[PDB]
Length: 456
Image (cartoon, rainbow, N blue to C red; front, side, top):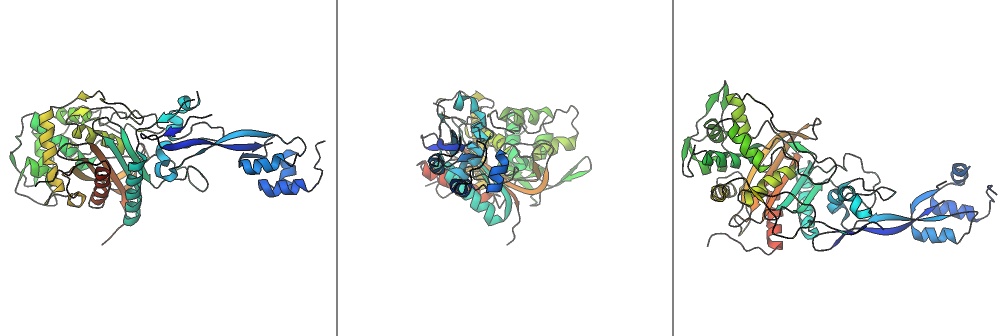
């Protein structure tokens, strides 16, 4: 009896349904052998030849009981355990699947194969109710945009629990027929990409802590050169405040903040928030991303590092980063299992310093920002849109237009960190993923009965 997997509210996600196994050595050529062939989908020639020892496995008991009451020569029925997944496609990648011998091969089924056999029940951090809402919005968004793929990871800022982890496309764990191997991969923990503009909140933090800038400081944001490379934003601005730099996603802005500090400044802050550090769930293929081990930093390299290039992250790794932003500089480990609060957290940045940067990040959601489509009605949100051009498992990167939105809500007192990723949207008519974050985060906020924190 393999253990029952449940969500945080005790709803069933994986249960063991019972299923049969079917196994004077000449075929009597009675009427029963034909009725056997019709039942097991096994021709007389094939049936006779394959035994001239298993015949059929993972067979419906109803058929199984119809076979017993033929009473054929030394036919023996063995008891097996097919896994039934009520959610199915919705949480295919988290739950995973089991093999024919009831051995964990993918998802938590493999991660907790020991506990679920050697057996008691598993209570996950995931909320089916949220996962369902997260998955639907993502699946619809990928289809609407005509995108190849899409990923959404939802983390609790306070507990570090994974509330949802939807991937599109998904697979049917109840029937694994006609689905490729590439579809099985959990793209939320395996596929890595250059984090890009999503690191710029961390740049502003470092610059504030290193005293390079005050929270009301204004910078010369005209285009300039570093080692014969022009640092320029598409949207050209004369002057921007530290707020404006995040608002407008000013490469010129962050590059000057970065080059005002030592090379090691960002390398430290990034590592503190958990860039290039193992997510440390049991899941197969879980990637720790890529991170510089280098020694000599050129001026251009220090600048491109502030733009969010020269390192790579899983959607889950980035969700943990923004979880640490929502907690106001408290780095908690990720949990796929339900946990009783309070969860012990390590402080990596001063509380009042991070809080001001979270307030600056609301301007991205507000008018003039690059993330206005992500705006929730009644809720203040602290988000950051970004873009990358290649994404895949380590050594298997494919050149795709990767659009994503990392954010935290509600801004007044954050409860959730969300990361949405739309992969290679082949659309016409960052700006692609901004709305998905909106629908998802908005739905999560109203579902958990959070109060709107919009101004009078």
